[PDB]
Length: 89
Image 1 (cartoon, rainbow, N blue to C red):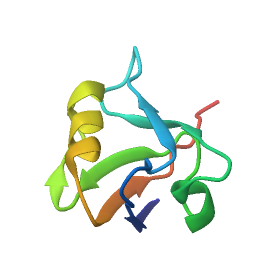
Image 2 (tube, rainbow, N blue to C red):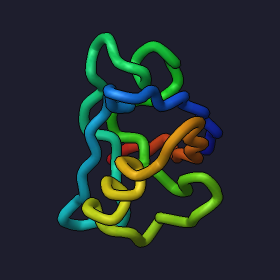
Image 3 (tube, rainbow, N blue to C red):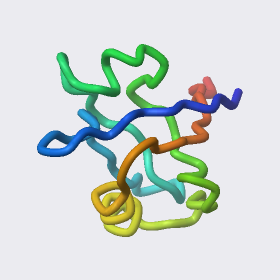
Image 4 (tube, rainbow, N blue to C red):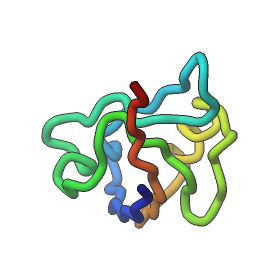
């Protein structure tokens, strides 16, 4: 389950989310969505989503620090492809 999401990054403010790695799976995942922020207001991103691609760059095997730095250095519209992550039981 995959979605494209476009967040308009504004000067002096963040995108309004945090991201984290996992111990038993590769990749980077949405861990918090700041109430009030850009990610929250756009209304598509969810806690647990995997960030798969950022402005066309594949980051499925990237590190938390790498994706965070990328997002921090990006300007304007940031286009994210994300994967909704289900839990197997």
